[PDB]
Length: 18
Image (cartoon, rainbow, N blue to C red):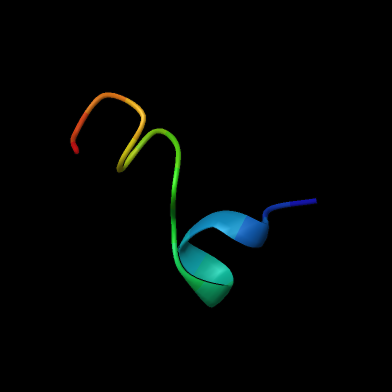
């Protein structure tokens, strides 16, 4: 459910922090 930081955050870490 948390494929972000797991394999590589691309939202809360990218979506807003590109």
